[PDB]
Image (cartoon, coloured by chain):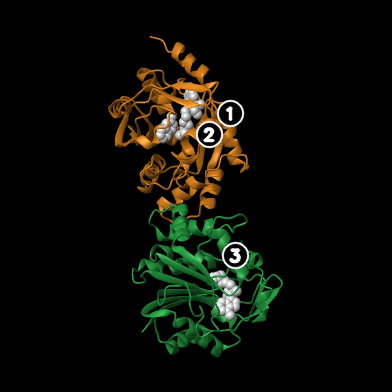
Chain colours: A green, B orange
Amino acid sequence: ASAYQRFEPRAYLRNNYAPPRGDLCNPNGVGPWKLRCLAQTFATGEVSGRTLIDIGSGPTVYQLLSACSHFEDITMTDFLEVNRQELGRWLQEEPGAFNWSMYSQHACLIEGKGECWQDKERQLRARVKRVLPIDVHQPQPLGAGSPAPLPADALVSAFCLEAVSPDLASFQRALDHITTLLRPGGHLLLIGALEESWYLAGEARLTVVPVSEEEVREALVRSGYKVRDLRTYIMPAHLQTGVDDVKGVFFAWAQKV
Amino acid sequence: PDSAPGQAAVASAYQRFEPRAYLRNNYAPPRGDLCNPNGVGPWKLRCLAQTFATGEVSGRTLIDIGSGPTVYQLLSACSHFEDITMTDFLEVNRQELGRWLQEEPGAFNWSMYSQHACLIEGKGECWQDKERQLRARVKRVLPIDVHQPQPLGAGSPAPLPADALVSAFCLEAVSPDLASFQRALDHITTLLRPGGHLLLIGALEESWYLAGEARLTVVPVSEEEVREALVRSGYKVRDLRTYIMPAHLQTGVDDVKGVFFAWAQKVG
Ligand SMILES: Nc1ncnc2c1ncn2[C@@H]1O[C@H](CSCC[C@H](N)C(=O)O)[C@@H](O)[C@H]1O
Ligand SMILES: Nc1ncnc2c1ncn2[C@@H]1O[C@H](CSCC[C@H](N)C(=O)O)[C@@H](O)[C@H]1O
Ligand SMILES: Nc1ccc2ncccc2c1
Ligand SMILES: Nc1ccc2ncccc2c1
């Protein structure tokens, strides 16, 4: 765990969200795939409500671009202060903010509603009410008197759980922990690395539990979800860059029962 | 009577035309605000996009008539033509384009327009790809004078005759009056092959617009005057639509009351 105290936000953003993995121009890349999964799911009109919490946001906002038009109250979270500050810099249009515009643009493209990317960002910035500390290893990840409206109508979490868990069972428990934040009948969108064991964030080398699609499925079932959808993206050779050993990416749409 | 005097006045007036001020006036916000779907920028792009989306306007060669310092008018066109000719009377506009072609930072930024075009064409094309393709398909930037019987001159570089023409806010902006406008339409029609297409966009009932120090005189035209001229020139009008300029978009940079878009096909 303590490895996360060397985690450099800018290095992680560079490693994953700048070219080559950050090139959205190629439709077969991982960036467009992730956005596509997010957009298609909300376009169904079945993931809706008032409040949403993003679990382990890190310094990234892309995972909420499509979500933001279905939820008026959004809570972003991370274990690290540096990440929350990086988020704050973008949410407040402060200096040095990461440029997410290509992603906003592509979400607008994919969604096909004719929306300009600036409106999309305006709405996202406006519906994120708070950026809060969080530790999924804790039975109450948000703590006791959290400002976050609970229970949430929906959850999003991308590349958090497996990346904070030494093994399957720890992964399963963290899942159990965040699931308590979710209202019954609510929805979870879970995104994560498949069969990954490490990734780099500057000086930080993080351990990851290698999970499979079937393991992810079973974990959700054991937690009280019906899996509405689970798709896999296989990482092409050209996006295997030395920043990690991720083999593929899973997308899960789960509904708490 | 005789065309020299007015054409002389026009040529004289454009010696003061400032591309940057014009770019700022029409293509930066508020008129350059692509977020409001009711705005004129989105309408113009939408007219182009929808027309090319029919699949009915295709071929090898396209000529843009009176390009000025702008490229937006070719964003949807560029996927349908291998060879694109851009053109203008003023060297300064041609250099402006040269600055965009070379992908210089000093160039005017059209990326909002590229993105919006990508957005409305609905193929999930990224804007850098659209731009890269426009830059590849523009084979030449030429001097042009629409008042000349041979607008491009004698033995021009352009592959003649073209399969399609585009022209935005040129003819009316350089014609002291209607007969001048008609003659200009007639002159550019000689560049188009029979059965070919002209996409014509322009200001309605405009008598002046500003380009820095230069204050240019425009012949005020109606939709019906536009239609008749096209018929008069040997076209069938396939589409003619009108945008009424919203009050909030009348900014003192001109007295334009509306914009027209004509899709016309040359009889032959
Ligand atoms: N014990 C813990 N509980 C909850 N989140 C944690 C955690 N330890 C580390 N994290 C956060 O988990 C994130 C993994 S990477 C950020 C993923 C981001 N959501 C995106 O989609 O790319 C990091 O931000 C990290 O700081
Ligand atoms: N005699 C002439 N023949 C052809 N084009 C001319 C001309 N005199 C001026 N022009 C060009 O007509 C343009 C009018 S402004 C329109 C520019 C651009 N097509 C747009 O859509 O914004 C200017 O670029 C001007 O220099
Ligand atoms: N460790 C990570 C985090 C995010 C990713 N997104 C796409 C592909 C691989 C990824 C690895
Ligand atoms: N003189 C001009 C040139 C371009 C325009 N585009 C939209 C509206 C008015 C316009 C006037």
- Does mark 1's beta carbon lie closer than 8 Å to ligand 2? no
Position in image of residue B150 (x %, y %): 47, 22
| Whether residue A194 is visible | no
Secondary-structure class at tag 2: loop
Q: How far apart are marks 1 and 2 (CA)?
A: 8 Å
Label 1 close to label 2 by CB (< 8 Å) = yes
| Whether residue A50 is visible | yes
Residue B77 vs A83, above or below: the answer is: above
Identify the subunit bearing mark 2.
Answer: B
Residue B92 numbered mark, or none: 1
Name the residue nearer the viewer: A244 or B4. Answer: A244
Q: How crowded is mark 1: few (under 14 residues within 10 Å), some or many (20 or more)?
A: some
Q: Earlier in the sequence, mark 1 or mark 2?
A: 2
- Does mark 2's beta carbon lie closer than 8 Å to ligand 2? yes
Disc 2 marks a residue whose amino acid type is: Pro
Position in image of residue B140 (x %, y %): 56, 35
Residue A85 numbered mark, or none: 3
Q: Which residue lies furthest to the right in this view?
A: A203
Front position among marks 1 and 3 = 3
